[PDB]
Length: 350
DNA sequence: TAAAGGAGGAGGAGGAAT
DNA sequence: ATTCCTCCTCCTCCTTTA
Ligand SMILES: Nc1ncnc2c1ncn2[C@@H]1O[C@H](CSCC[C@H](N)C(=O)O)[C@@H](O)[C@H]1O
Image 1 (tube, rainbow, N blue to C red):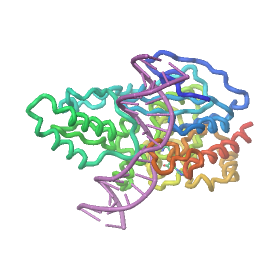
Image 2: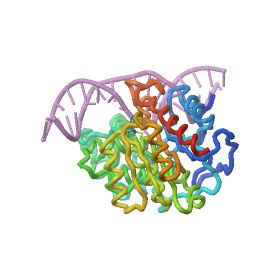
Image 3: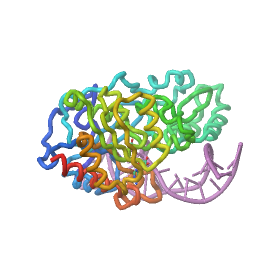
Image 4: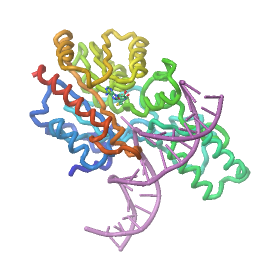
């Protein structure tokens, strides 16, 4: 009957009380290897109960990423890592809208009481939706405040699509370079490959919060001085890889699995534009990743130190008005593939 | 054609009252 | 144990536009 923690500090978050330095982790879940699983907090009833059950009955750590970046992101994490001696990433992130968007405060209305953004999703606001707002705020420009019925209109639209003020009565949606900056990714991390503006948003919505993830993975730097061998499933745009990079942890081996070709080239770009010492191997479909080739890469590079990944949440997310069936869905059922692969690596690390 | 736009809620959290 | 109220969701799918 597990419920959501209030507040979502998990086992603790930087600059916030309620920190815990130890937990009673069951014997069966003891590594090696270390695994790290991420997914949406707000799921249909009985989802996290099933997920945790297959992951050795480990109680999930729910963390809202609002304690790291300016945008909210209520996520649940399951892992077998130590909690003690965690540290955060540098530089410190912009917590409030006032800090993240300095150039917006010249245009920001006094009647907009927001200091935090909502969740960065795959869909963004339209460039004609911002026109419908400007023509509705233009007549009342002479007076300090517009009518309440108009005021209710713009506010509801802003909170829905996460709009920011960039000009006189101009509320435009976020730009990809700003989304990357909020999530922790470097600017133009997803720009290359002739990627369309729409596809950049879809690959950014489905992504980690680097500042949050790296905070958890920070307990791996002193214990692995020589580096690590990572096996990332559903790697996307390399949320876990960017986290380790800024954590100053050497990455000997990275075996990534990604069905999307454009997402694969992003990681390859980040690998070459960083001049990484280690080696990158890229797989496509996770349903074709046989355990023969798994144990093949195992005996050559010497096992896997970390198995990080975040299963698809298309059937779990509340935004889905068509096919929100839970782990019974088409995309979200691939979580068991994570379990299968994770079961194979454990078999040899024993 | 490839890209942007628009139409379209259920479902719980988290309240602050009894 | 109650209400009643406000808010937020790693979104799918059809249509329009350049
Ligand atoms: N059958 C499959 N095999 C491998 N990857 C898949 C897959 N189905 C979907 N995916 C990938 O899973 C991703 C969503 S989950 C990825 C989360 C996030 N991008 C991260 O950094 O971890 C999508 O980018 C998609 O390309």
